[PDB]
Image (cartoon, rainbow over the protein chains, first blue to last red):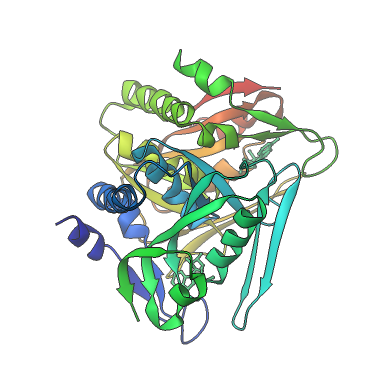
Length: 177
Length: 177
Ligand SMILES: Nc1ncnc2c1ncn2[C@@H]1O[C@H](COP(=O)(O)O)[C@@H](O)[C@H]1O
Ligand SMILES: Nc1ncnc2c1ncn2[C@@H]1O[C@H](COP(=O)(O)O)[C@@H](O)[C@H]1O
C-alpha cells in the first residue's frame, strides 16, 4: 500500500538534539522517490476528500515543511505560501514569538502573503507539542486567512499537539508515542 | 514561454537584509502553480539533456533549496538528499564551515547520505558569491560523491559565483547583476 511506503522510511535517532528525545528523521522518505510520491499522494487525497476545492493555498513551514509544501500544492494544483523563521523574509512581516516550556516557536510571514478570507492548509514534517503550527495558525489568522487544516507526515501523540491546535483540524500519516 | 512564467515571478527588495543589498524573492514563483511547474520543468529538461540518466540524486540546500529539490528530483524520477545548516541533522555528519569576506557558509551532511561514486546535482534558489554551493560541493566530495552540476533559479553574475564553482558546471534560469 501507499502508507507502507512511508511507514518503512522513517528513521529514529535517540538523544537528539538533546538527551531523552527521539528524533524522527524523514530523510529516507525524501531519498526514496516512491516513498515521497506516496506521502504527497496520501496527503493530497485526504485534503481533496475533506475540503474539495475550497483550499486556496498550501503553507509550508521553515524548514522541513518546505520539503513537502510545494509538491503537495502542485498535486492539488495550488500555489504555496511561505512561513519562515524570523528575520528571513523581506518586506513588512507579522511575527509570532512563543516561549513554551521545552522550546521556542518563533515564525514570521509577509503581510501581503494572503488576502482576507483566503483558505489555507498548513504543512510541516512532524507535529510534536504543536507550538510551531499553532504559531503559524496565529499568523494566518492575523492576516484574516482561514486555516482549514494542519497536516504532517509524523505525529507524536503523547505531546498532545492535536489538542493544542483545536479547533483547527489535524491529520497525520504516521503516529508515534 | 516557460521561462517567461518564471521571469515575471521574481520580486526585488532593496536594502535587505543589509543596506546596499537587493534581495531577490522567489516567493511569487512558489505562489504561482504554473510558474513553479515551469521552473521545475526547465531545470529538469536541462539536466536530462545534459546528463541523461547518470544522475543518482538531487541535493537540496537548507532552506530555500528545499523548495525546489524534492520537486526537481520527482520530475527526474530521483530521490532527494539533504544538505542542512549545521546542528540540524541527526547522526554522524561532515561539516563545512567557511568564512568568506561578506558572510559565512556553514553547512552539514549525514555521513551515510551518499555512497562513493554516486552522482549528484545540487540545487538552491539563488547563486551569489558561490560560497554556499561551494561548501556543499566540498561536503559531497568528502563523501567521494561526484557533483555533476549545480543549478539555481537566479544568478547574480557580478558576484562571480560561476568562477568559484569551476570546474563544477553551473546553470541558472535567470541572471541579474
Ligand atoms: N522528536 C522529533 N523528531 C524530529 N523533528 C521534531 C521532533 N520534535 C519536534 N520536531 C520539530 O519541531 C517542529 C514542531 O514541533 P512542535 O512546535 O513542538 O509541535 C517541527 O519543525 C518538527 O519537525
Ligand atoms: N541578493 C540575494 N537575494 C536573495 N537570496 C540571496 C541573495 N544573496 C545571497 N542569497 C542566499 O545566499 C545563499 C547563497 O549565497 P552565496 O553563498 O553567496 O552564493 C542562498 O541561500 C541564497 O538564496
